[PDB]
Length: 233
Ligand SMILES: [Br-]
Ligand SMILES: [Br-]
Ligand SMILES: [Br-]
Ligand SMILES: [Br-]
Image 1 (cartoon, helix red, strand yellow):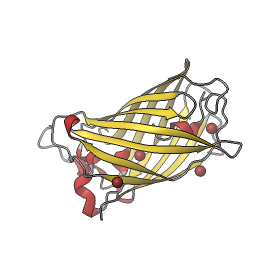
Image 2 (spheres, rainbow, N blue to C red):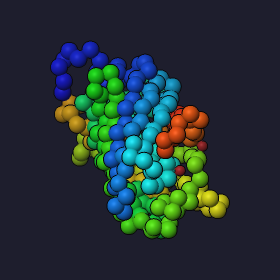
Image 3 (tube, helix red, strand yellow):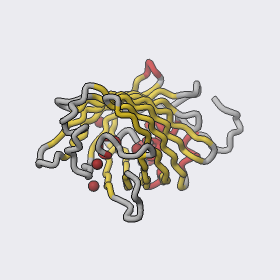
């Protein structure tokens, strides 16, 4: 645990608007890149507003393939489900979020992130490793639409890791009208040793919109996103 006093513990840190910083270093089939993002989250409304920039030049993969990787503590948990909010309960010390993302008939991403507070800022620091991609596939060939769909993200307790398991399927729209499936396997573990809320089975409901900043000439993505916990009552 932490200094008891630490003015705000877990949920108390998210009652207002919180600045967010995201830092990602990636390597996909040897194409190395980095991304930074900045914005804010308002968990009362499940609301995220973020702008991401590829800091190394051109992004070697489509932006939509990075949305899931690039802060589930900003989810709106209904009052009646407050006891199932693992993500906020881990704060401020935070949690490790690990994924494997299988792109159907193509490669996989494996990601490891630490999500925690650094002062007033909620920070998501990620490493991403992609292998087994087709150089002419939908990912390295940049054949995905710059858009995003709504999804449910399914959560269960992992009592052995004092954490959670998460799984879900993302369907990316291909430029020919077809669909590129990306199956997500996820686990989160607290960084601290204190108690955390281990949830009953439930899900998060996501809506996401991607756009561009008309005055931004670097390779970038503007993201608006709303996230709401559901599935209990
Ligand atoms: Br793109
Ligand atoms: Br999120
Ligand atoms: Br969109
Ligand atoms: Br469920």
